[PDB]
Image 1 (cartoon, rainbow, N blue to C red):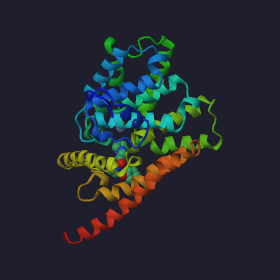
Image 2 (cartoon, rainbow, N blue to C red):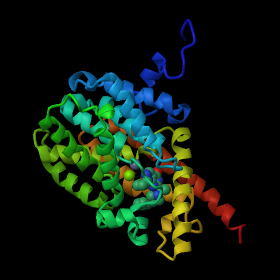
Image 3 (cartoon, rainbow, N blue to C red):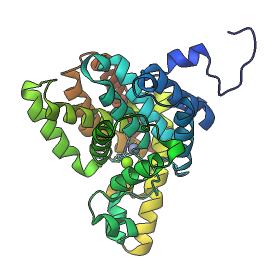
Image 4 (cartoon, protein in one colour):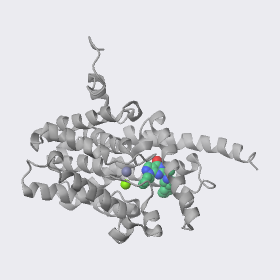
Length: 328
Ligand SMILES: C[C@H](c1nc2c(cnn2C2CCCC2)c(=O)[nH]1)N1CC(Oc2ccccc2)C1
Ligand SMILES: [Mg+2]
Ligand SMILES: [Zn+2]
């Protein structure tokens, strides 16, 4: 709705507004547009101002991060954009600037962007079972998450990419420790442990307690990481096919190499519907339910689409079941 046409990398006022909501269609944008979106988030959240981030360094850093994301069906730059856009949406929805310091917002945003850097498209179970260079390097302790972390700090060590160059050493150490904790917390093998620890703190939550806040930040990055089903159906649905494509690539390789195959990755056992019913019911809904205890606004905005999505996949399952009996 402007007097002239502006290039794609110059975000329209409408795009800037839409970016604050979890309804934002992540599929409409090319890498350069998503890069402009992330850059806007840093300026808009006051991170550029409060951490004296050089605006050109912010751009070079984001471009370098983008280049270090592999062209995987799911674990790609668009996924990191989803996680960072969901984190940004949660800052506004949950009024996180009232509860968190600017350093904490910086940690949450930087970890969301960096969390899946240089992902090979084969999970930790593959790395460990196949005894890969990564599993050997990390001694089977979250090999991928440790690698995403190392790559993040390797990018940040390059002077033209150092968005933390004007932050005192004590501030850097604080941000570094926080980012490591958050990226490592994304390992789904640790889900039950992190959920139990958070629920334990949820008995009498304290925003002044550093340990309570560390666990809340861990839950926040975890929420954003697996948040696809929270998005509108049309935006959410294509991500499942992307992930199954990655899961099938791994399970085929494991079968060929004689390694164990996870049933949720097996082409002969998995369907888009059955995989999502379980994940929404037993992972997504319980996690957002605990967040709702601190942030009641999460129920209407995030649990509601999850309830709808669960109900839609249950309808699709009945169709798949009717279809699969004719297959034999
Ligand atoms: C396909 C399903 C699944 N997995 C997802 C989603 C988002 N992130 N992830 C994973 C990417 C790497 C970490 C998490 C998602 O929407 N569905 N998968 C999960 C499995 O289903 C279950 C079911 C119950 C409990 C745990 C996993 C089939
Ligand atoms: Mg990951
Ligand atoms: Zn991820």
